[PDB]
Amino acid sequence: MKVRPSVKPICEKCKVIKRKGKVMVICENPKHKQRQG
Amino acid sequence: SRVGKKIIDIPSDVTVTFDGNHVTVKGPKGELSRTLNERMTFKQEENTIEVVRPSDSKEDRTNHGTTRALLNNMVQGVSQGYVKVLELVGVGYRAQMQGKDLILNVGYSHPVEIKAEENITFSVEKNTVVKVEGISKEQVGALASNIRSVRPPEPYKGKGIRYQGEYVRRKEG
Amino acid sequence: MIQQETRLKVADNSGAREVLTIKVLGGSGRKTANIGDVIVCTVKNATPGGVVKKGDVVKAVIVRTKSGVRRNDGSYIKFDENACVIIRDDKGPRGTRIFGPVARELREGNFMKIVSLAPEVL
Amino acid sequence: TKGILGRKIGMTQVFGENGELIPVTVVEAKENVVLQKKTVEVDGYNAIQVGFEDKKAYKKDAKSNKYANKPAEGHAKKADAAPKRFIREFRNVDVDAYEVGQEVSVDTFVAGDVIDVTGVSKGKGFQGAIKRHGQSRGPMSHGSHFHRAPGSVGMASDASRVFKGQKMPGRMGGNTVTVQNLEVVQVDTENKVILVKGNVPGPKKGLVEIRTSIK
RNA sequence: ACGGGAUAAGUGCUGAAAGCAUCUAAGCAUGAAGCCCCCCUCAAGAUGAGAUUUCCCAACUUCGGUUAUAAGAUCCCUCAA
RNA sequence: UUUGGCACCUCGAUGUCGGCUCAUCGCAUCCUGGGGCUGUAGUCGGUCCCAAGGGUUGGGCUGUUCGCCCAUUAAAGCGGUACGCGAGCUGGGUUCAGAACGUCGUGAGACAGUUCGGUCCCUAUCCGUCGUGGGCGUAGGAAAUUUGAGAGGAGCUGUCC
RNA sequence: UUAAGUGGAAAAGGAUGUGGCGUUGCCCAGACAACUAGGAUGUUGGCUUAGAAGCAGCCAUCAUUUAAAGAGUGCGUAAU
């Protein structure tokens, strides 16, 4: 996981979603995994 | 609800027993009772369960699709049921039946014992592939995830528990 | 009952005669050691020649304390002085000749070489 | 389950298997009887009430607690029994296994049973912080005028007060304390005594409550 | 250093909004020395003052007030766990 | 929590630093616990997230706060509470009278740069705290046994097979 | 209007979570997902670079079996 106030997509597959009031990004690879905080 | 517009939901050889706040379904493998929702409404014309959403609100628009999918799942699992399959890739990693319960050996200092549940049937193919037949899609998925969580796939070699068609990115460490 | 700063005679032929103890090891806050326990120590008086030289920092095992030991049968054993033997960080001694008597509680700590080399074991 | 009462007699030692030495407390558990059976439908909780040491019957112009009073006599009359010094309740037992008037015999306990033992601590009186708590004493030389007092009790203007639980002097002594997981060594039915491994709280000829451990 | 529940991070199942996908919106699980309970002690001045068992009850007398007095305490005295 | 800026309370007095005794809070986590990612093969390690329950050593040279070192430890955390705590203790430091070195000054003397020496008061009224009693209350009076709304305590960790 | 107890503590920046106002384009000759059905070849042709034939890095980036595809969008890639 990669926590940071600035979440952005790195690759095209890396989409953006919300869960429990927090912004996250989901990619096939987990290195692009992020959440906002 | 584009899926709620496909809410014909014709049962083949199965009854559909509404009871107001909840609904029961009975077929070949009956007894599927669920307290679905009240904001939605239902109807049975002859052999078609049609669901309707009021007020065209956001919440109703979501709940329409959710309830329709749940109802279709319930009737389809009462009719045909569901089956979830997986396999143990490993060396010395072996599972087997114990009547109703399952037993597994993965190289711990103690084997693992899976206690079965209702409307659930395990099936060992060749002590390396396993199937779980049931009627509740959520239940079979839950149990499959539970058993695979015991020893998930290892990345460097692939040792662990994995589905029949799951991919595992293997790192050459 | 060996604490920091106690002085012990040495009961082997390693080269040291008198030794001062620096630390009782084990846990944090360990204050006192007794028979079978390991200490680190300094040699304050050495014999000419010998393997170990004055000013060296070494490890030792305690044998024959004065405030001796109780046993499960309710028996006790005591001695008239405090003594130690210097070891090779494998429960083996640096010398080859143990002097004086030795307690029987050394068998429980895997000091069989010292027990074998010793005279009367009590 | 399996509770009884007794008096502490003293400490001795005994020899076990392979010659091992065992310090032992001897407890006189004598003439225990059941006086009452409390229930959930009446009293709100299931328990038996046990009386241990017999005293004298009622007497006119009696001044001491050696002689029962009319209430105690009537209470010990329902059960066909005599009046008793000490009365205590047990909630850990099965209430149906006992009967009013029944005699609780020491042979309820057998060797190897792990037990809890309850009693009042001895008694010491007004004691300071060095003894009542484990406080360190100040220097006895180098110009010191601070030996056995307690140190500071608070900080400063911020919190211009003393908090509760500050560990000052006061009375130390008799408070009830249980010790857990002692075991029975043997039982002598002719003298009606139990031998407990270890030591129990309280002075000699003092009441102790023995019962079975949970763990 | 146990064990029960509910939870955090996190892993999930089912599943729409958005014919797909999605751990979440509705729902079902798991999940920590942390929270609550379990363990020990104090505790009805808990003015909300609780409950059980047993004992006692006036001769007048609105048995109020009375001398009485009962159950029960105390004064006093010998003592200490 | 620093060095400062301002000069709002206190100059008919608000005790200065270290150390001892005694604690209490926060988390921006030293150990233990749970997890994600890894340029994580295992052993490990690095980074990030959750988390404050408990625990968090003894000595040498230091006035020393600070710092270096010796041996341990699962770890030797960072801070606040009048840089916590002198009507609880020392008084090593600084600074008062004495004296001396160096420097400066015509000099009396100064530096704050060094050095030896150099008096630490108080019978607790109120709040507060630790214990321990008397009075009254609780729809009759008493002896005994109790429930438990609440409150406090406890909570650590290692090596070996 | 808001669904956070915001209300009842700030910022650079980051995101969808909803309302409003316009402009503009997408379509029964069926839009926007998603199924599968085609993935090319003379051709890496050339400098042909560790060979590389979507990839040391500069391309030369031409017809098109075809209702319809590129001297390969793109997964890639030791190269495939």
Image: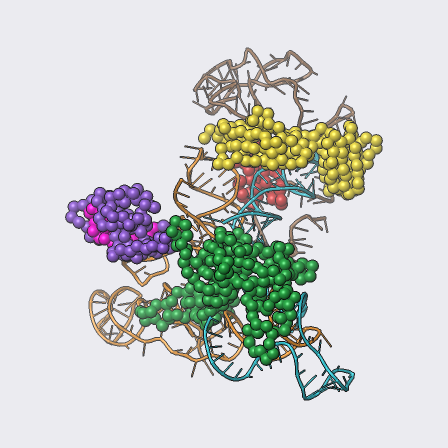
Chain colours: A red, B yellow, C purple, D green, E cyan, F orange, G brown
Q: As drawn, is G17 to the left or to the right of B159?
A: right
Front residue of this view, candidates G71 and C47:
C47
Q: Quick one: quadrant of the N terminus of chain C? A: bottom left
Q: As drawn, is D23 to the left or to the right of A4?
A: left
Query: In the image, what residue occupies the spot 30% across and 57% down?
Result: C67
Residue F55 at x, y percent in the picture = 44, 55
Count of labels shown? 0
Residue C83 at x, y percent in the picture = 25, 52
Residue B32 at x, y percent in the picture = 73, 36
Is residue C12 part of the magenta span, yes or no? Answer: yes
Front residue of this view, candidates F28 and F150:
F150
Q: Quadrant of residue D80?
A: bottom right
Q: Is residue D121 above or below residue B29?
A: below
Front residue of this view, candidates D211 and F153:
D211
Q: Which residues are magenta?
A: C8-25
Is residue D10 part of the magenta span, yes or no? Answer: no
**Residue farthest along the front direction in this orientation:** D190
Query: In the image, what residue occupies the spot 65% across and 31% down?
Result: B121
